[PDB]
Image (cartoon, grey):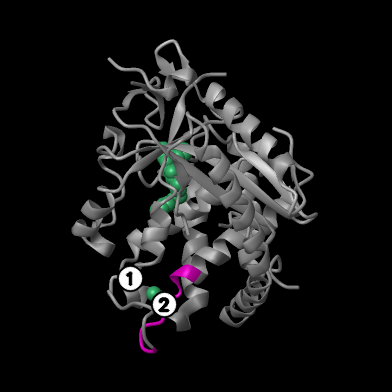
Amino acid sequence: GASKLRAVLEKLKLSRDDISTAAGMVKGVVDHLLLRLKCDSAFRGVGLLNTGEHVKISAPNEFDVMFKLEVPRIQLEEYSNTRAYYFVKFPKENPLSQFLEGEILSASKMLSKFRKIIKEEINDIKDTDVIMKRKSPAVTLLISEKISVDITLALESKSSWPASTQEGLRIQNWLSAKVRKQLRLKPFYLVPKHAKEGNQEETWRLSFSHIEKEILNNHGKSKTCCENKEEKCCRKDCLKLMKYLLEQLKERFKDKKHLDKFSSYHVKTAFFHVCTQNPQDSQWDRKDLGLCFDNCVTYFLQCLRTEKLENYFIPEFNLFSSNLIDKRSKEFLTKQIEYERNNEFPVFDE
Ligand SMILES: O=c1cc(CNc2ccccc2F)[nH]c2nc(NCc3ccccc3Cl)nn12
Ligand SMILES: [Zn+2]
């Protein structure tokens, strides 16, 4: 119960203080690469995207970074009616035309020049040992023998969010409509997709990876939630436990393929739906950690059984569509999570 879940969280906290030094090595290499990238005519306006980092909290040495590139006067064209994937289209020509394939922006061309640069600069680094790993649209580096960094390049648009997000980000009941309006004034992002996901096609995918940070840092119905003794909630802790539960289950079954398609996306999306459904800070009281986590678990199970997990920004897109994850995989994860819940989560102890 809550006592055990608390113990897990204190365990993870100790390993977080020991990767401050590893974060320094990452920031060192990242800033070096942003500097050499800015010398390129195509990537001149590249920059770091503020997102908080760690997709894996059971592997404190694996890091995740996003570089953004602003592309002004951008025209988007939705692929099929997939809602999430888009072709990128544009009198005067500019350096980005070297990435055009016909009249659309090629992610392959752009990723290829992106990779060639980093690989060239990685070899030029002599103050630390850093290797590049084999190609999956991101670039992955190994610093020392333990630390690894995934670098994703995203296009940034400061124009209005695409129309498929119009009924999404439904946080009005929790954080108020004016916060939703504010968030929707922030830019949006487009990333290259996998050859795994989708149909090779030069479509880009909507990304809102900058939004989680905005909400997690201002997460209460109360403006002072988690800012004094009398207002301690367990939202952050429940998201951490949900993430750890999926990471642990995927490790336990890494030999089978049955869980390859589940990721922290699904847990996060399910978490923030529970925050929408339970908007009151009193539904997240620190003393009720065990009950609050159980709510998160049972909500996730319900999504699994009904095969419905709406993306948070594009509700028409079902992350748990059988078109994406087959019925048998959800049923399996349901079985494992039900077993965990029923046995006070033995996947959690030492
Ligand atoms: O960066 C993130 C993070 C989350 C995680 N959830 C989440 C984050 C912040 C606040 C609330 C949340 F529930 N979801 C997400 N969806 C998209 N793009 C849309 C999309 C991406 C991929 C496939 C289909 C679709 Cl339609 N980006 N993106
Ligand atoms: Zn709080």
**Above-or-below relation of 167 to 103:** below
Amino acid carrying label 1: it is Gly
- Which of the four quarters of the rendered structure image does ligand 1 lie in? top left
Identified at 55% across, 65% down, the residue is 240
Identified at 72% across, 72% down, the residue is 349
Identified at 44% across, 10% down, the residue is 102
Q: Which mark is residue 220?
A: 1
Q: Residue tagged by mark 2?
A: 233
Residue 293 in view of the camera: no
**Above-or-below relation of 38 to 3:** above
Residue 225 in view of the camera: yes
**Do the residues under discs 2 and 1 have CB atoms within 8 angstroms?**
yes
Q: Position of residue 253 (x, y in %)?
A: 75, 49
Quarter of the N terminus within the rendering:
bottom right
Front residue of this view, candidates 10 and 118 = 118
Furthest-top residue in this view: 102
Q: Position of residue 266 (x, y in %)?
A: 51, 48
Q: Position of residue 288 (x, y in %)?
A: 46, 79
Position of residue 162 in the picture relative to residue 275 (left or right): left
Front residue of this view, candidates 41 and 19 = 41
Asked which quadrant contains residue 283, the reply is bottom left
Furthest-bottom residue in this view: 229
Q: Which residues are magenta?
A: 229-236
Q: Position of residue 296 (x, y in %)?
A: 48, 63
Identified at 60% across, 75% down, the residue is 9
Badge 2 residue CB within 8 Å of ligand 2: yes
